[PDB]
Length: 330
Figure 1 (tube, one colour):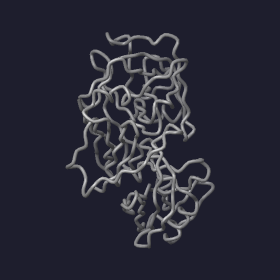
Figure 2 (figure 1 turned 60 degrees about the vertical axis):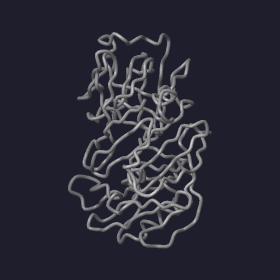
Figure 3 (figure 1 turned 180 degrees about the horizontal axis):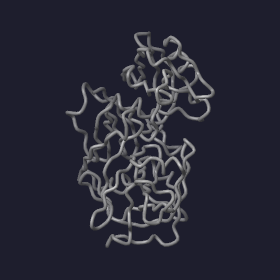
Figure 4 (figure 1 turned 90 degrees about the vertical axis):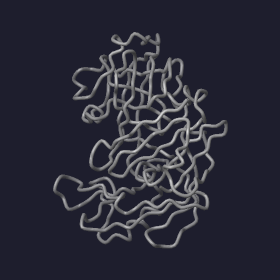
């Protein structure tokens, strides 16, 4: 089997992407944030504290003839941005782009933190990291991809995120019309539960490539590109007036600037992030200070190849017995 679903930016900055997902019988369609940095499929629901729902579409398990309470199971998750959610668990039928999994754990939120409530466009998350990170207790649950894998034509999914435009998540096949050149594959460590790999270096604008190993994760659920402070300083030094602002919480730059591109290495290959992809707009409405799309990872503990990087490529998440990642230009 295969599936194919369009993923759409939630706003004009590409802060995140939503993909429609069918849950239950009859189908209830919710728009989920597909997150290769986490491993829980959780939804706003009829169980979510009413004051914490503000415009999201909810899953109502009592209206699904295929929903079953997973008795005793609870979940609780905290994300790198400080947001969180928790609740109980049902199993139900879940379909993405024509690919159907029966018995998928659907984690129903009883509580969500303010940033989730405040984002009316995201009805939940669909985790695509390794199932060892799933938070369900006392019986850990499998991701949608893990459950689908055996049925797929090939044990892969691909992320093709758009810049200010829709893109595609495919399951079970590689669309050879969706990229240019060849795909370069690189080793993955699953030891932390992430799609963790090592970039071979970087360049700033038209500058020379610096060969240096950068371990990090491919994370569709993180907006920006978080890299070591040395690398980020070298980038922003090429932008007149750019500076790190403690009060804003990262590098800012004059909105009048034209940003240089940023290149990262995948083996001997190179992915070029155009400068425009690094502009995240005014820090506050009407400000002439703009927020940068490349930020330091120094306070995180891990480097993160988030959407800023991933949307410059066609990305293969290869879930074969030894997982690997593939990157192609597009």
